[PDB]
Image (tube, coloured by chain):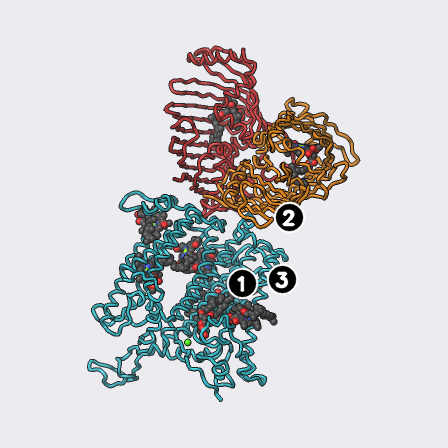
Chain colours: A orange, B cyan, C red
C-alpha cells in the first residue's frame, strides 16, 4: 500500500558577486495531514525592503491568513531588524493577532544575542565547510498589548494572579508556549528552551485604553542542529538587499491530502565555497528534522523534478546526486539517486546534496 | 375527509423516498454483492445464450422440421458460422449435423449458467461455504485457486479497488488464454498469425493473454493512484466505468461496420445474400374465404401460390432483401445506441455522486485533477461556453447546407440543383474513410459533430451544475436533489433543472445523432430533406454529383419508401402501430399538465364513489393515483425514447435497399 | 513475504439524551511485538457500578491477568471514585499485586486536582471543538502496604535508607517509576512528570502485621496532548452511569504477532456537537501517540472494517473519511480513505475522523 506525491523545484542564479536566486516549489501529496483538525488551509507572505545602506536596517513584513476547521485565523507582523554587532541584533516592530471575532494588536522592542561556546582557528583551517556550530540565543522582549477587549483584561489579570500565587511560573510557562506537538519538536531538533525571566508586568496608560506591558527575557541553546544559532549571519542578508526581496507561499490540507505552492527571490541562495567556486546554500537542518516528525506516517512514492538554472558562462564542477539530464545552462534533477535523496529528506534525513558551479 | 385525502398525495410526493427502481442501488449493497449480482446475471446470460442457440436449429437431430428464422439468432449466425458451430449448407445432412452442435452448446451453456447462478446466490448471501470441505472462505483475504494465487499474487487478495486491477487483469488473461485453448482444442482453429482467417483469432487470443498477464502483474506491484477518490465510493467508480464502457461499445459498433463487410468477412456476412430466409411474421400463403381443407385436402376451396401448404411462411430472397447488411445494421446500431446510453448514464450516475459530495462538503477535499480542475465556476462557463459556441456554429453551418440543398432541389425561389452544394464533399485527406465520397458524407460527419456537441451540453451541465449553477448562485438557490422537478412558478419558473432532467434532455437531444446513424447506415441521403421524389430536381442528384450508388430516399422521402415493405408485413406493421402508440402517450406526462390530471383524478374517484353508492349498496374508494413530475419525466422519457427506437428497428429490419445503379437525370 | 494485519470495529448507539454506546474491536497482526520478552499475554477487565445518584460515587474494579515469559503476573484494584468539584476528585480503594510466588496488598486514600492554565471565553466562543487544553494534575497519595513478606520489609528498609542518605531521591525516583521505555513515552506525549514529594514514610501497626505507610504527593503537566488533563470531565461519566458499564479486553503476543480482543459498553461514546447534532467522542490522542512508538517498526498492509450502528431515525449528516457502504440503520467503513486513516493512526498519526449524526 503506497500513495504518490508529485513535486517540482527551480533555482535561478545571477553571476558576479550577486547571491540573488529565484526559488519556485510546487508539491502535491495524497496522505492525510497529522493535524488533528481538518481541513486546515494557510497562505504566508514575507517582503523585505532595505531602508538605508549605511545603517543596514531593513523593513520586514509577514501576513498569515489561515482557516483552521472553519475558524479564520490571521497574524500580521511589521518589523525593523538591523545588525548592531556580530552577536547582537535589535528589531522594532508592530503586529496584530485575529482569531474569528477576536483580535488584539501588539508593539515590541526586542534584541537577540547569539554566542558560540567556542571559536577556534583550527576548526576553520581544517574544515572547509562546517555544518554544526554550538551556541545559544538570548531574547530581550518588551511587549505592548492594549487591553481593549473584556477577555484581554481577564487574560492579564489571570496572568498576574498566576505569577503571584505560583512559584513555578518560569518553568510551567514552557508547557503553554509550546502547545501540543510543539513541545516534542524541541527535543527533536536538539534545542533546549531555557526558563523565561519576567523583568516586569506593569499596566501603563495609553491614549486609546489601559495597556498591559510585559518586559521579559529568555534564552535557548542549540547543540549545533539549530540553524538560527549555527547560521546567525546567513539568515539575514541585509547588506546584500540591493533591491526588495519577497517569499510567497501557501498550502491546502484536509483528510484527502496536502497541496503546497512556494515562490520568491532573496539573497543568500548562493555562497562562496573556496577556490573561486560558488555553491547553493547548505539545506536548513531544522525544517528537515521538523518534517521527519510528520513525514513518517504514510508509505509514499516520490515524483520530484528539480530544475536549476545557472548564469551565462557558469558550469557545475561537481554535484552529488548527479543531474539526470542537462540543457545547455539549465541542469535537471529527477529520478534514481535524487528521488532517493528526496525520500531521505522528506522523512527527516539531512544527507548532503552539494552543487559547485564555477565560472 | 381532507386529512385522509392529503395522507395519500403525501404518499406520492416529490420529496426523497424509496422507489421500486432504486432497490439495487450501489449505496445499499457492499462489494461482495456487486460480485454476486454480476455472477448471477452471467448465469442468466448463459441461459439466454443457450436459447439463441436452440432457436437457430432448422432441422432437428431426428430429422424433423425445427424452428423458423428469428432476428435473435440471425445477429449471431455469422459468428457461429465463423466458429464452425453453424454452417451455411444446402445439404440437409450438414443442416442436421449443425443442429446437434448448437443443441450441444446450448446444453453446455445451461450447465455453466447453472453453476454461475449457484456461485451467485452464495456470494450474494455471504454463505460462501465449501460443501465438500466444511471450511468457509474469506472475501478480504483468500488464496485465489490455491497454488496459482501464491506464485503471482504473493498469496494475497486485493483489499482496495486500485489493487484489484492487477488481479482482475490476471483473471482476464485466463479468459484470453481460455478461449485460445477452446478454439484450438474444441473448435480446431490452430493459431496461424495471418489476419484474413479465423485462425488469427486464436493467435491474438494468446498475444492478448500475454499482454494482460504482464500488465496484470505490473498493476499488482504498482497499483495506479489515478482517481483515488473512486476507491472510496462504489458509484463513483461504477460511473467512470460506465462512461468508459459506452465509448468502448460505440467503438465496437464502428469497427463491426467496417469489418463485417470486408473481403475477409465475406464467408460469414456477405455469404448470407445467397440464402432463403423464413422470418417469423412475414407474409404467409393466403387462403380464400370459403377454404376448408379436409382429410382429402384441397376440396371446396382455393389458396394462394399452391406450391406451399395453407398458412405457411413464404420464402424470402436474401439478395433482394439485403440480408447481409440488415444483420450488419442490427448489430452495429445495437452496440452504438447502447454505447451512447451507457455514456449518458455514466455522467448521470457520476453527477449523482457529485451531488452527494457537494452536500457533504467532500467536494473541496478531493485532490484528483479529475475534480480539482473542475471546481472553478469561471472555468465551467468557459468549457460550457465553448461547447455551446461550437454546437451553434456547427448545427447552423450544416443545417443551412441541408436546407439550401433542399431548396435548390425543389426549384424554390427559381434556384436549380446547380446552385446547391453538390461540389462539397470530404477533403482528399479524409476520402479513405468513405466509399464513393460525396456531400452525403460531408454532411454526416458534421451532423454527428453537431449531434454530439448538442447532447454534450446536457452532459457538461450534469458534471458542473449538480448542486449549484452560476444562475442559482445568483438567485441564491441550492439543488438539494438529483430528481426534483422544478422550484415552482417563481422566477418565470425553473422546471427541468435537476441532473436527472438534464439526463432526459441528453437522451432526447441524442435521438438526432442516434437517427443520423440509422439513416446513414441504411444508404439514405442526408444532404437533402427531399431526395428521389418525383419532383423538380430530386432525381437529378445521382448525375449532378456523379454518385456510384443510388441512395434509397431523402430525410422525408425515407418514411415513404422504407415503409412499403413494412406495410406488406403483418408483424412489422404491428410494431409501427405499437411503437407509435407508446410514443405519443409520453406527451401526457411530459407536458406541464401534472396538476390537471390530479384534479381530474379527484373527479374520477368522486364519481366512482357516487356511482357505486347510487347503484350498489357498497362504497367504492380506489383513490385514483397520479404520477409526480419527476416520476412523469421518467415514464415520459421511457415512452418517448422507447417508442422512438421501437420503430427505428423497422427501418433496419425492413431490408437494405441502397443500390449500385445511379439514376440518369429525369430530363 | 509481505506483512498484513486484520481488524474489525463496531459502535452501537442509543437515541435521546443517552450517551451509551457498545464498542467491539478484533485485531490480528503478523509482526513481532517490541517487548524484549516473549511470549507475553494479557487479559484486562473493568466494571463500574453506580453506588448512589445524589453523591455521584461509583465503584470501579480492575483485574490484570498477564503471563510474561512464563511468569504469572496479576494486579487487582477495587476503588470508589466520586466528583468533589470541577477540579478535585477523591478515590478510596484497595488492590493486590502478585508476581509468581510473590504477592502484596495495598490500600489507598487519594485525591486528584486538575487545573487549566487559562480559561478564556473567546476560545470557547471561537472554537466549536477544542482539542488541545493546557493543564496540570496533582495526586495526593496515602499508600498502606502491610510488610508481611521478608522481601517487603527489605524493600521498605532500603527505601528509608535511600531517602536518608540520598538528597536526589525526589528526582531519581522518576527513573525507577517509569521502567525501560515508559520514560521515553513521557516526552513523546508532551507530558512532564514533576518530582515526587514525600509527606511521610511511617510504619504503623496493623492487626495482621507491621504496615509500612507512605503519604506522598506529585504533579504532572500536559502541553495539551494528554487526555487526562485536556479531557478531565469526559473520562468520568459517573452521572450518566444509570446502569453498570463494563469494558473487557485481552491480547496474545509472541515472535509471530499479536492477537487482540476488546468489547464493552459505557457512556460518553456520544457527545453533543452543537446545532442539535450528535457526534462520536474525539479519539484519545495519548493512545495513538503511544502506539506510534511501537507501530513504526514493520511495513504492513491494513484490512480494517468499521461497522457503526445508529439509533432508529438517526442518520449521519457528515463523515470524513466517508463510509464505503450504507445498509439501512448501519453504516460501514472499509478501504480507500479509511484504510489510509488506519495506517495513519496505527503509526502514531492523530488525524481527525468525524461522524455527525442528527435525528
Ligand atoms: C525559530 C527559532 C527561534 C527564533 C529565531 C530568531 C531569529 C533568527 C532572530 C529572531 C529575533 C527576534 N525574535 Mg526570536 N526566535 C524564536 C522565538 C521567539 C519568540 C517566541 C514566540 O518564543 C519571540 C517573541 C521572539 C522574538 C523575537 C523578536 C524580538 C526578534 C524579531 C522577530 C521578528 O521580527 O519576526 C518577524 C516575524 C515573522 C513571522 C517572521 C518569521 C520568519 C521565519 C521564521 C523564517 C522566514 C524566512 C524564510 C526562511 C526566508 C525568507 C527570505 C525573505 C527575504 C524574508 N522570538 C525561536 C526560539 N528570533 C531576530 C533578532 O535578532 O532581533 C534583534 C532575529 O534575527
Ligand atoms: C435509463 C437511463 C440511464 C439510467 C438512469 C437511472 C435512473 C433514472 C435511476 C437509475 C438507478 C440505478 N441505476 Mg442507472 N441508468 C442507466 C444505466 C445503468 C446501468 C447500465 C445497464 O449500464 C446500470 C448497471 C445502472 C445502475 C443503476 C443502479 C445504481 C440504480 C438502481 C437500479 C435499480 O434498482 O433498477 C431497477 C431494478 C430492477 C430489477 C428493474 C429493471 C432494471 C434493469 C436491470 C436495468 C438496470 C438499469 C436501469 C436504468 C435501472 C432503472 C430503471 C428505472 C425504470 C429508470 N444504471 C442509463 C445510463 N438509473 C436509480 C438510482 O438510484 O440512481 C441513483 C435511479 O433512480
Ligand atoms: C495515566 C495518566 C495519569 C493518571 C490519570 C488519572 C486520572 C484520569 C485520575 C486518576 C486518579 C487517581 N490516580 Mg492517577 N494517573 C497517573 C498516575 C498515577 C500513579 C502512578 C503509579 O504514578 C498513581 C499511584 C496514581 C493514583 C491515583 C489514584 C489516587 C486515583 C484513582 C486511581 C484508580 O482508581 O485507578 C483505578 C485502577 C485502574 C487500573 C484503572 C485504569 C484505567 C485506565 C487508565 C483507563 C480505563 C478506562 C477505559 C479507557 C474506558 C473504560 C470505561 C469503563 C466504564 C471503566 N495515579 C498518570 C500520571 N489518575 C483519579 C482521581 O481523580 O482520583 C480522585 C482519576 O480520575
Ligand atoms: C460492462 C459491464 C458494465 C455493467 C453491467 C451491468 C448491468 C447491465 C447490470 C449490472 C448490475 C449491477 N452492477 Mg455492474 N457493470 C459494470 C460495472 C460495475 C461496477 C464498477 C465499479 O465498475 C459496479 C460497482 C457495478 C455494480 C452493479 C450493481 C449496481 C448491480 C448488481 C446488483 C444486482 O445484480 O441486483 N457494476 C459495467 C459498467 N451491471 C445489474 C443490476 O441489477 O443493475 C441495476 C445489471 O442488470
Ligand atoms: C459468461 C456467461 C455465459 C456465457 C455467455 C456468452 C455470451 C454473452 C456470448 C457467448 C458466446 C460464446 N460462448 Mg458462452 N458463456 C458462458 C460460458 C462459456 C464457456 C465456458 C468456459 O464455460 C465456453 C467455452 C463458451 C463458449 C462460447 C462460444 C461458443 C461463443 C464465442 C465465445 C467468444 O468469442 O469468446 C471470446 C472471449 C474472450 C476473448 C474472453 C475475454 C473477453 C474480454 C474480457 C472482453 C471483450 C470486451 C472488452 C471490454 C473490449 C475492450 C478492451 C477494454 C480496454 C478492456 N461459453 C457462460 C454460461 N457466451 C458468444 C456468442 O454466442 O456469440 C455469437 C457471446 O457473445
Ligand atoms: C464463475 C465462478 C465465480 C464464483 C462463483 C463461486 C462458486 C461456484 C463458489 C464460490 C464460493 C467461494 N467464492 Mg466466489 N466466484 C467467483 C469469484 C470469486 C472471487 C474473486 C473476486 O475472484 C473470490 C475471492 C471468491 C471467493 C469465494 C471463496 C472464498 C468461496 C469458497 C468455497 C468454495 O467452494 O471455494 C472454492 C474456491 C476457493 C477456496 C477460492 C479460490 C479459488 C477461486 C477464486 C474460486 C472461484 C472460481 C474460479 C475463479 C473459476 C475459474 C476462472 C477461470 C478464469 C476460467 N469468489 C467466480 C468468478 N464462488 C463458494 C460458495 O459460495 O460456496 C457456497 C463456491 O462453491
Ligand atoms: C469551408 C469550411 C467549412 C467546413 C468544411 C469541411 C471540409 C471541407 C472538411 C471538413 C471536415 C471536418 N469538419 Mg467541417 N467545416 C466547417 C466547420 C466545422 C466545424 C465548426 C462548427 O466550426 C466543426 C466542428 C467541423 C468539424 C469537422 C470534422 C468532422 C472534420 C475535421 C477536419 C476539417 O475540418 O478539415 C478542413 C478544415 C478546414 C479547411 C477549415 C476549418 C475552419 C474551422 C474548423 C471553422 C470554420 C469557420 C467557422 C465555421 C465559421 C462559422 C461561423 C458561423 C457563421 C456562426 N467543421 C465549415 C462550415 N469540414 C472534413 C471531413 O472529414 O468532412 C467529412 C473535411 O474534409
Ligand atoms: C391514448 C391516449 C390518451 C388517453 C386514453 C387519455 C385519457 C385520459 N386523459 Mg389524457 N392526455 C393525452 C393522451 C391520452 N389521455 C395526451 C397525449 C395529453 C397531452 C396533451 C394528455 C393530457 C391530459 C391532461 C392534461 C388531462 C388528461 C386527462 C385524462 C383523463 C380524463 C378523461 C376521462 O376521464 O376519460 C376519457 C376516456 C377514456 C380514458 C377512455 C379510455 C380510452 C382507452 C380505451 C384507454 C386505454 C388505451 C390505452 C392507450 C392502453 C395502453 C396500451 C399500452 C401498450 C400503451 C383520461 C384518463 C385529465 C384527467 O382527469 O387526468 C386524470 C387531465 O386533466 N389528459
Ligand atoms: C448521442 C449523439 C450521438 C449519437 C451516436 C453517434 C456515434 C456514432 C459515431 C459516428 C460513426 C457512425 C457509425 C457507423 C460507422 C460507419 O458508417 O462508418 C463508415 C463510414 C462511411 O461508410 C459508408 O457508409 C455509406 C452509408 O451511406 C456511404 O454510402 C459510403 O459512402 C460510406 O463509405 O462512416 C464514417 O466514415 C463515419 C462518418 C462520421 C465521421 C465522424 C466525425 C466525427 C469526428 C470528429 C469529432 C466528433 C466528436 C465531437 C465531440 C463531441
Ligand atoms: C365514472 C367516472 C369515470 C372514471 C373511471 C375511470 C377513468 C379512467 C381510468 C382508466 C383509463 C386510463 C387508461 C390509460 C390512460 C392513460 O393513457 O394515462 C396516461 C398515463 C398518465 O397517468 P396519470 O399520472 O395521468 O394517472 C392516471 C390515473 O389517474 C388513472 O386514471 O401515462 C402513464 O402512465 C405513462 C406510462 C407509465 C409506464 C411507462 C413505461 C415506459 C415503457 C413502455 C413499455 C410498455 C408500456 C406498458 C406499461 C403498462
Ligand atoms: S408546470 Fe411543472 S415544471 Fe412547470 S413550473 Fe409547474 S411544477 Fe415546475
Ligand atoms: Ca430500409
Label 2 beta carbon less than 8 Å to ligand 1: no
The quadrant of the picture occupied by the C terminus of chain A is: top right
Whether B409 is drawn above or below A222: the answer is below
Q: Give the left or right position of residue A344, taking residue A246 as reference.
A: left
Q: For mark 1, what is the residue?
A: B458
Q: Chain of mark 1?
A: B
Displayed quadrant of residue A67 = top right
Q: Residue at x 40, y 28 (%)?
A: C42
Q: Residue furthest bottom?
A: B667
Q: Chain of mark 3?
A: B
Give the secondary structure at mark 2: loop
Label 1 beta carbon less than 8 Å to ligand 9: no
Q: CA distance from mark 2 to mark 1?
A: 54 Å
**Labelled pair 2, 1 in contact (Cβ < 8 Å):** no
Q: Position of residue A211 (x, y in %)?
A: 75, 32
Q: CA distance from mark 3 to mark 1?
A: 21 Å
Q: Give the left or right position of residue B357, taking residue A240 as reference.
A: left
Q: Residue at x 61, y 47 (%)?
A: A309
Q: Residue at x 32, y 44 (%)?
A: B136
Kindly report which numbered mark, 2 or 1, lies closer to the viewer in this rendering: 2
Viewer-side residue, B196 vs A298: B196
Q: CA distance from mark 2 to mark 3?
A: 65 Å
Q: Chain of mark 2?
A: A
Viewer-side residue, B454 vs C153: B454
Q: For mark 2, what is the residue?
A: A312
Whether residue B260 appears in this view of the structure is yes
Crowd class of label 2 (few under 14; some 14 to 19; many from 20; radius 10 Å): few
Q: For mark 3, what is the residue?
A: B491
Displayed quadrant of residue B250 = bottom left
Kindly report which numbered mark, 3 or 1, lies closer to the viewer in this rendering: 1
Amino acid at each position: 500500500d503506497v500513495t504518490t506525491a508529485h513535486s517540482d523545484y527551480e533555482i535561478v542564479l545571477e553571476g558576479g558577486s550577486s547571491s540573488w536566486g529565484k526559488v519556485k516549489a510546487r508539491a502535491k501529496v495524497n496522505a492525510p495531514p497529522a493535524s488533528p483538525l481538518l481541513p486546515a488551509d494557510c497562505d504566508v507572505k514575507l517582503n523585505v525592503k532595505p531602508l538605508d545602506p549605511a545603517k543596514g536596517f531593513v523593513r520586514i513584513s509577514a501576513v498569515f491568513e489561515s482557516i483552521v476547521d472553519s475558524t479564520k485565523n490571521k497574524l500580521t507582523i511589521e518589523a525593523d531588524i538591523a545588525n548592531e554587532t556580530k552577536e547582537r541584533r535589535i528589531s522594532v516592530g508592530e503586529g496584530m493577532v485575529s482569531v474569528g471575532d477576536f483580535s488584539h494588536t501588539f508593539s515590541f522592542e526586542g534584541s537577540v544575542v547569539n554566542l558560540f561556546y567556542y571559536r577556534s582557528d583550527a576548526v576553520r583551517r581544517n574544515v572547509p565547510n562546517p555544518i554544526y556550530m554550538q551556541g545559544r540565543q538570548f531574547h530581550d522582549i518588551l511587549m505592548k498589548v492594549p487591553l481593549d477587549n473584556n477577555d484581554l483584561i481577564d487574560t492579564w489579570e489571570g496572568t498576574v494572579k498566576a505569577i503571584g500565587s505560583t512559584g513555578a511560573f518560569n518553568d510551567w510557562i514552557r508547557d503553554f508556549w509550546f502547545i501540543g506537538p510543539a513541545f516534542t519538536a524541541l527535543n527533536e531538533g536538539g534545542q533546549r528552551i531555557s526558563r523565561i525571566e519576567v523583568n516586569g508586568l506593569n499596566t501603563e496608560s495609553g491614549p486609546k485604553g489601559p495597556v498591559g506591558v510585559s518586559r521579559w527575557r529568555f534564552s535557548h541553546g542549540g547543540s549545533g542542529m539549530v540553524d538560527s544559532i549555527s547560521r546567525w549571519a546567513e539568515l539575514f542578508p541585509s547588506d546584500k538587499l540591493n533591491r526588495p526581496a519577497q517569499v510567497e507561499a501557501g498550502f491546502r490540507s484536509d483528510s484527502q491530502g496536502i497541496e503546497v505552492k512556494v515562490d520568491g527571490e532573496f539573497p543568500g541562495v548562493s555562497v562562496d565555497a573556496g577556490g573561486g567556486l560558488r555553491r547553493i546554500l547548505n539545506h536548513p537542518l531544522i525544517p528537515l528534522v521538523h518534517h521527519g516528525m510528520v513525514g513518517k506516517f504514510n508509505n509514499f512514492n516520490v515524483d520530484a523534478q528539480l530544475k536549476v538554472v545557472l548564469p551565462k558562462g557558469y558550469k557545475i564542477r561537481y554535484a552529488a546526486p548527479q543531474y539526470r539530464s542537462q540543457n545547455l545552462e539549465e541542469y535537471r534533477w529527477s529520478g534514481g539517486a535524487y528521488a532517493r535523496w528526496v525520500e531521505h529528506v522528506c522523512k527527516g534525513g539531512v544527507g548532503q546534496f552539494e552543487i559547485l558551479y564555477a565560472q | 375527509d381532507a386529512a385522509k385525502m392529503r395522507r395519500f398525495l403525501f404518499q406520492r410526493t416529490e420529496t426523497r423516498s424509496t422507489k421500486w427502481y432504486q432497490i439495487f442501488d450501489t449505496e445499499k449493497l457492499d462489494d461482495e454483492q456487486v460480485v454476486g449480482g454480476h455472477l448471477a446475471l452471467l448465469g442468466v446470460l448463459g441461459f439466454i445464450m443457450g436459447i439463441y442457440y436452440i432457436s437457430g436449429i432448422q432441422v432437428f437431430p431426428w430429422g424433423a422440421p425445427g424452428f423458423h428464422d428469428n432476428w435473435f439468432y440471425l445477429t449471431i449466425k455469422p459468428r457461429m458460422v465463423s466458429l464452425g458451430i453453424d454452417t451455411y449448407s444446402t445439404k440437409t445432412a450438414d443442416l442436421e449435423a449443425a443442429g446437434a452442435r448448437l443443441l450441444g452448446w446450448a446444453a453446455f451453456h445451461f450447465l455453466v449458467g447453472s453453476v454461475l447462478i449457484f456461485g451467485g446466490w452464495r456470494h450474494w448471501t455471504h454463505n460462501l461455504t465449501n460443501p465438500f470441505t466444511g471450511r468457509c472462505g474469506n472475501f478480504r483475504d483468500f488464496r485465489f485457486l490455491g497454488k496459482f494465487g501464491d506464485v503471482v499474487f504473493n498469496g494475497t487478495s486485493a483489499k482496495s479497488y486500485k489493487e484489484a486491477l492487477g488481479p482482475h487483469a490476471v483473471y482476464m488473461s485466463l479468459l484470453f488464454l481460455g478461449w485460445g485453448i477452446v478454439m484450438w482444442a474444441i473448435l480446431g482453429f490452430a493459431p496461424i498469425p495471418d489476419f484474413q482467417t479465423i485462425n488469427s483469432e486464436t493467435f491474438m487470443s494468446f498475444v492478448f493473454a500475454v499482454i494482460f498477464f504482464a500488465l496484470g502483474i505490473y498493476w499488482w506491484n504498482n497499483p495506479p493512484n489515478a482517481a483515488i477518490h473512486l476507491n472510496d465510493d462504489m458509484k463513483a467508480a461504477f460511473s467512470v466505468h460506465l462512461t468508459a464502457i459506452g465509448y468502448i461499445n460505440i467503438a465496437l459498433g464502428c469497427i463491426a461496420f467496417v469489418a463485417f463487410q470486408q473481403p475477409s468477412f465475406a464467408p460469414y456476412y456477405k455469404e448470407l445474400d445467397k440464402l432463403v430466409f423464413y422470418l417469423y411474421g412475414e407474409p404467409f400463403n393466403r387462403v380464400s374465404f370459403n377454404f376448408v381443407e379436409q382429410g382429402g385436402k384441397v376440396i371446396s376451396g382455393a389458396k394462394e401460390f399452391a406450391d406451399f401448404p395453407a398458412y405457411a411462411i413464404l420464402p424470402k430472397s436474401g439478395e433482394a432483401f439485403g440480408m447481409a447488411r440488415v444483420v450488419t445494421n442490427l448489430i452495429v446500431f445495437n452496440h452504438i445506441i447502447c454505447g451512447v446510453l451507457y455514456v449518458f448514464a455514466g455522467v448521470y450516475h457520476g453527477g449523482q455522486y457529485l451531488l452527494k459530495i457537494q452536500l457533504n462538503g467532500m467536494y473541496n477535499q478531493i485532490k484528483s485533477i479529475w475534480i480539482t480542475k473542475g471546481r472553478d465556476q469561471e472555468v465551467q462557463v468557459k468549457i460550457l461556453g465553448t461547447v455551446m459556441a461550437l454546437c451553434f456554429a456547427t448545427m447552423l453551418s450544416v443545417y443551412a447546407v441541408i436546407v439550401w440543398n433542399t431548396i435548390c432541389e425543389l426549384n424554390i425561389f427559381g434556384t436549380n440543383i446547380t446552385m446547391s452544394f453538390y461540389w462539397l464533399k470530404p477533403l482528399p485527406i479524409f476520402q479513405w474513410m468513405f466509399a464513393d465520397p460525396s456531400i452525403n458524407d460531408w454532411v454526416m460527419a458534421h451532423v454527428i459533430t453537431a449531434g454530439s456537441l448538442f447532447s454534450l451540453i446536457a452532459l457538461v451541465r450534469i458534471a458542473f451544475f449538480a448542486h449549484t449553477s452560476p444562475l442559482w448562485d445568483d438567485l441564491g438557490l441550492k439543488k438539494n436533489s438529483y430528481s426534483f422537478p422544478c422550484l415552482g412558478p417563481v422566477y418565470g419558473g425553473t422546471c427541468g433543472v435537476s441532473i436527472q432532467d438534464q439526463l432526459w434532455f441528453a437522451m432526447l437531444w441524442g435521438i438526432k445523432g442516434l437517427s443520423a446513424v440509422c439513416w446513414y447506415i441504411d444508404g439514405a441521403w442526408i444532404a437533402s430533406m427531399m431526395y428521389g421524389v418525383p419532383a423538380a430536381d430530386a432525381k437529378a442528384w445521382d448525375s449532378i454529383a456523379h454518385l456510384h450508388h443510388h441512395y434509397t430516399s431523402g430525410i422525408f422521402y425515407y418514411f415513404w419508401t422504407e415503409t412499403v415493405t413494412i406495410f406488406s408485413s403483418s408483424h412489422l406493421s404491428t410494431i409501427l402501430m405499437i411503437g407509435h402508440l407508446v410514443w405519443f402517450i409520453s406527451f401526457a406526462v411530459w407536458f406541464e399538465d401534472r396538476g390537471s390530471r390530479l384534479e381530474g383524478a379527484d373527479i374520477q374517484t368522486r364519481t366512482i364513489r357516487w356511482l357505486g353508492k347510487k347503484f350498489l349498496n357498497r362504497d367504492v374508494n380506489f383513490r385514483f393515483p397520479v404520477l409526480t413530475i419527476s416520476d412523469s419525466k421518467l415514464a415520459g422519457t421511457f415512452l418517448y425514447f422507447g417508442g422512438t427506437f421501437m420503430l427505428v428497428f423497422l427501418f433496419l429490419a425492413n431490408g437494405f435497399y441502397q443500390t449500385n445503379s445511379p439514376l440518369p437525370p429525369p430530363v
